[PDB]
Length: 81
Length: 81
Image 1 (cartoon, rainbow over the protein chains, first blue to last red):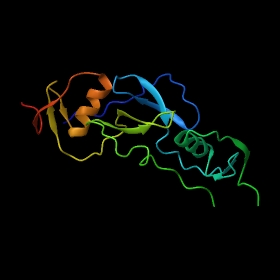
Image 2 (tube, each protein chain N blue to C red; image 1 turned 135 degrees about the horizontal axis):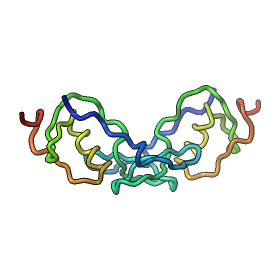
Image 3 (spheres, rainbow over the protein chains, first blue to last red; image 1 turned 60 degrees about the vertical axis):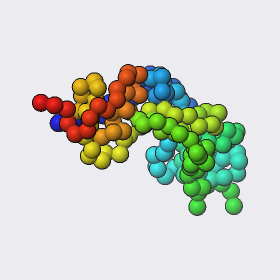
């Protein structure tokens, strides 16, 4: 009855955005990388250089992207102690 | 047990993005407007200058934003005929 929603797959092929970032469409109709809106909540805990434990790989880098800081995974699973 | 996800509300207050656009965070940690990822699927049909019928106000402008074209609502409800 009404027009069915358009996709960004076309504008966002084949775009590479790092971990914690994904591809979206600017007001000019062209692809950018921005911080990921919501990470898929797979349970895959991870420990950051910042000493924090994150739910998964995406969440660690998404946080890095929101804060403009330098977080990386140093080891997987929860942080020590 | 793990750190709970951060929000963009802080970076995106108080940002104004037009219809069909919303606010997200760039790789530099600052707010932009980009095309809305998914419009809330409220049923509020609308007819565009482009002669197409859209599910709602957001969907018409989101399409405008993805195509870089000049769509506006000329009247609400489905298009004629």
